[PDB]
Length: 176
Image (cartoon, rainbow, N blue to C red; front, side, top):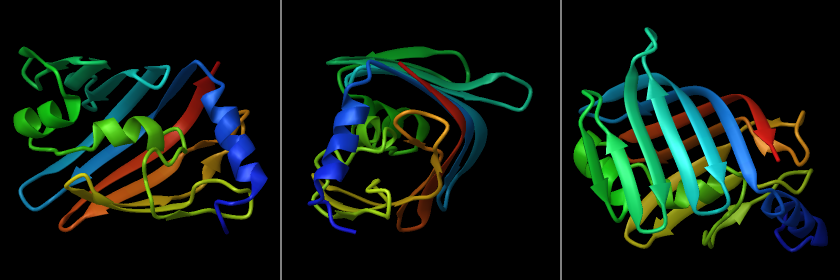
């Protein structure tokens, strides 16, 4: 489908009209040197503030990161807290996972962000993203959306780049 439809724009308007977003589920990070599997919890207020939490089956925190414009705190899988200006930069350097946090804060909401190459589906909802810019590269595939929310929010997504893929499966969402 084409991103021209005046609907795909209203939906983006729908999503962007929300103030808070909250989802959770299973997170899996896979590369050649690592394999991360954990429950994840993503809370977000606005387009600039969010908290990503990764927890072990036991409940132990494998990773906690709270981001705000120009200020991010990252808590170790050990418990050691670090602070920086860029989250995308911090996740990579201290955990090995160069997760595109700065772009994800848009894509997780089912928004393109600055993506210049994507597609839609029947319902005029972001379905595929081919990102190769700002020095980074990621192929984002949007699976089934959570339609128990208004507007529907993604409940399935896979981002891949080379030998590394990040899979997100949402159990549910709570938007306001």
